[PDB]
Image (spheres, helix red, strand yellow):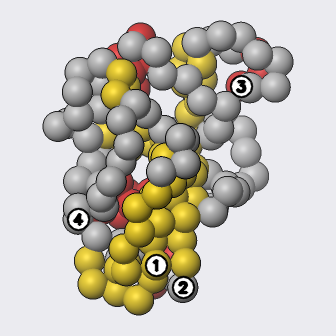
């Protein structure tokens, strides 16, 4: 088994994780994935502070309670040109990326590489963390606690 996790810089501890290059994370997998990073699903307040420090993506992802895209610059193909924390209102479907919040991260922008998944558990999957600069870390383990996600 192989899982790739592409991660962004952290902004006030908040970062984005995309699994396997496609929208593929359920709400329960999202929480378990953040836990593997010693992190939690961000609150809206945490995500607003991250936005204010420079965080934006062009991908839907879970926070606690909603699915969002943080936007700084208006772009027609990202969140229908909105700025701010854009909240997904209407969708048929259930699988997105996720955001995670690590309280121990630096207070502003941190673009250093992520080099561990400190709270993954014993398991058979090769999990690879891929940073935007291409640097990679891999370990054998598991993070999904719900059978329905596996």
Secondary structure beneath label 1: strand
Residue 126: which numbered mark, if any? 1
Secondary structure beneath label 2: loop
Q: Is residue 74 above or below residue 62?
A: above
Q: CA distance from mark 2 to mark 4?
A: 19 Å
- N-term-proximal mark, 2 vs 4: 2
Residue 48's spot in the image, x, y percent? Answer: 40, 18
Between circles 3 and 4, the one closer to the viewer is 4
Q: Is residue 3 above or below residue 56?
A: below
Residue matched to label 4: 119
Residue matched to label 3: 79
- N-term-proximal mark, 3 vs 4: 3
Residue 24's spot in the image, x, y percent? Answer: 63, 61
Between circles 3 and 2, the one closer to the viewer is 2
Between circles 4 and 1, the one closer to the viewer is 1
Residue count near mark 2 (Cα–Cα under 10 Å), binned few <14, some 14–19, many ≥20: few
Residue count near mark 1 (Cα–Cα under 10 Å), binned few <14, some 14–19, many ≥20: some
Q: CA distance from mark 3 to mark 1?
A: 33 Å
- N-term-proximal mark, 3 vs 1: 3
Residue sitting at x 41%, y 11%: 52
Residue sitting at x 73%, y 45%: 91
């Amino acid at each position: 088994q192989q899982i790739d996790l592409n991660v962004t810089c952290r902004y006030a501890g908040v970062f984005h994780v995309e699994k396997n290059g496609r929208y593929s994370i359920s709400r329960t997998e999202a929480a378990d994935l953040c836990q593997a990073f010693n992190s939690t699903l961000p609150t809206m307040d945490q995500m607003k502070l991250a936005l204010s420090k420079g965080f934006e993506t062009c991908r839907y992802g879970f926070i606690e309670g909603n699915v969002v895209i943080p936007r700084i610059h208006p772009n027609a193909i990202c969140a229908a040109n909105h700025t701010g924390v854009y909240i997904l209102v209407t969708s048929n479907t259930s699988h997105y990326d996720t955001y995670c919040f690590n309280a121990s991260a630096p207070p502003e922008e941190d673009c250093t590489s992520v080099t561990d998944l400190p709270n993954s558990f014993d398991g058979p999957v090769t999990i690879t963390i891929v940073n935007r600069d291409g640097t990679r870390y891999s370990k054998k383990g598991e993070y999904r606690t719900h059978q329905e996600d596996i």
